[PDB]
Length: 162
Ligand SMILES: [Cl-]
Ligand SMILES: [Cl-]
Image (cartoon, rainbow, N blue to C red):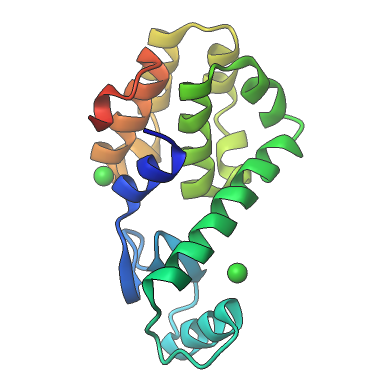
């Protein structure tokens, strides 16, 4: 298992514009297009992301290209962030994947707001970070996915995904 397989499980694949759990226009493997209610605004972000006239539909290869870019941008956002980088460097490989999953979902600004959880992850207080992570809008809105990520941070294994 790895970050690509983990995120593909959590996010799914859809080849046609759709609204995510928040009601935002999304396509591919969790690639957020725009928070605006306008479908025309989403189609135009899509054409621009892909470099052609999509009419709201993309192929599998294009979905995978966006996906690759987004995973890469999530990693590089972690490393440029003063709050995230120290935590990330302190973690083993499996739990590093859990951090990327969260950033991918909620952006680096969002995760960097999990100050107390971050401090506990850094101190390797796994059970306590799990409890504090669960006290969040994130967990209450998307509990199945959140539990999978929390379990990964708690155990250091891919068990929640196997
Ligand atoms: Cl893009
Ligand atoms: Cl969920």
